Image (cartoon, rainbow, N blue to C red):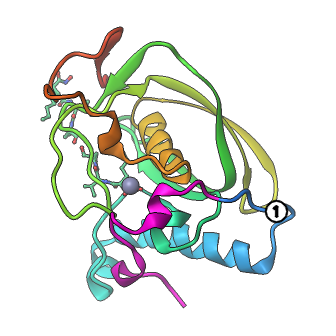
Amino acid sequence: HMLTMKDVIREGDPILRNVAEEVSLPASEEDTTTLKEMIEFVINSQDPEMAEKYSLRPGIGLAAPQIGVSKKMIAVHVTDADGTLYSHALFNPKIISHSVERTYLQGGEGCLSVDREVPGYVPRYTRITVKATSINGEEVKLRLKGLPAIVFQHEIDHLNGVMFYDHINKENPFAAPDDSKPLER
Ligand SMILES: CCCCC[C@H](CC(=O)NO)C(=O)N[C@H](C(=O)N1CCC[C@H]1CO)C(C)C
Ligand SMILES: CCCCC[C@H](CC(=O)NO)C(=O)N[C@H](C(=O)N1CCC[C@H]1CO)C(C)C
Ligand SMILES: [Zn+2]
């Protein structure tokens, strides 16, 4: 069994606004399988062949709530400008520290759960330290910046019932956030 867009729920579903439940670790086969299918989905969505074979909208991350599972699980598969790949399948991911300084994609953010465009900068912390447990069972401590840090914040926001547009400015989507700068290479 594998995930497709049919499994992705859209905004309006209360689950997207609830706080995902902590995953009991060591993880069960069920939760492991859920997470395995999540990272498979994200990676397949970036392969033209597979994306068409299952009509998948390309994306660089996914949170369990998005597929109807209210548990703390995320999948991230993003490559930065330097060609550095950040591929993670995680249980109970949490930001233990974030920079005061912020950043943002000038073209905004999109979400697989949102069938519409919401223009405006989505302020994000430039640097974050994340602690979680990999699908492989090992605890991990990741220090991210730039695009990878942005994707992690977006996915973890999903686990706390937060949507990307909740961060967009009030009646001035393009105002420069205090102490910040557009995403750098
Ligand atoms: C940048 C924050 C992380 C985005 C994660 C989403 C996937 C998602 O909804 N996760 O919960 C995605 O890939 N969204 C894409 C997106 O918003 N992107 C992809 C490149 C950067 C940004 C556009 O500015 C669109 C194209 C589906
Ligand atoms: C509407 C978008 C306008 C963004 C313009 C900046 C221009 C710049 O000053 N770069 O250093 C850019 O290309 N930035 C990149 C960017 O946003 N890109 C590069 C490829 C496309 C787009 C990401 O969606 C970085 C931040 C990743
Ligand atoms: Zn999303």
Q: Residue at x 54, y 46 (%)?
A: 156
- The quadrant in which the N terminus is found is bottom right
Q: Is residue 60 left or right of residue 110?
A: right
Q: Position of residue 115 (x, y in %)?
A: 21, 64
Residue type at tag 1? Ser
Q: Is residue 140 left or right of residue 118?
A: right
Mark 1 packing: few (<14 Cα in 10 Å), some, or many (20+)? few
Image height check: is 128 above or below 21? above
Q: From the top left corner, tell me how far across and down residue 101 is, in percent.
A: 44, 13
Q: Residue furthest top?
A: 179
Q: In which quadrant will I find the C terminus?
A: top left
Name the foreground residue: 154 vs 86.
154
Position of residue 26 in the picture relative to residue 127 (left or right):
right
Q: Is residue 13 above or below residue 80?
A: below
Q: Residue at x 35, y 23 (%)?
A: 103
Residue at horizontal 59%, vertical 66%?
Answer: 70
Number of numbered discs visible in the structure rendering = 1
Q: Which residues are magenta?
A: 1-20
Residue at the image position 17 percent from the left and 19 percent from the top? 175
Ligand 2 shown in quarter: top left
The majority secondary structure of the magenta stretch comes to loop
Does the segment drawn in magenta span residue 33? Answer: no
Q: Residue furthest bottom?
A: 1
Question: Is-magenta flag for residue 10?
Answer: yes
Q: Is mark 1 within 8 Å of ligand 1?
A: no
Q: Which residue is mark 1?
A: 24
Is residue 7 positioned above or below 176 on the image?
Answer: below
Q: Secondary structure at mark 1?
A: loop
Q: Image quadrant of residue 171? A: top left
Residue 87 place in picture, x, y as percent: 54, 53
